[PDB]
Length: 32
Image (cartoon, rainbow, N blue to C red; front, side):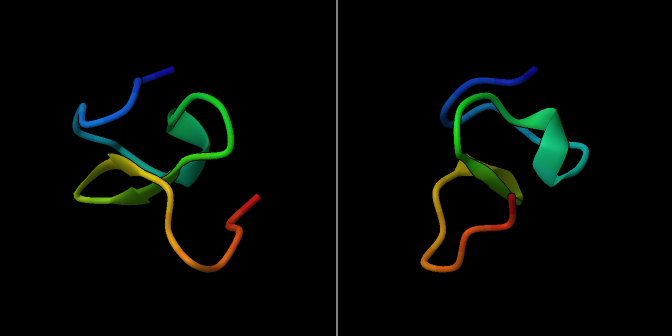
């Protein structure tokens, strides 16, 4: 998975509970 601040292909491509918003970042809403 991609870590914080890395570009994301999709939400589940991001590590932790991060979501995809251009980059892997935690949004307000939990995508997972």
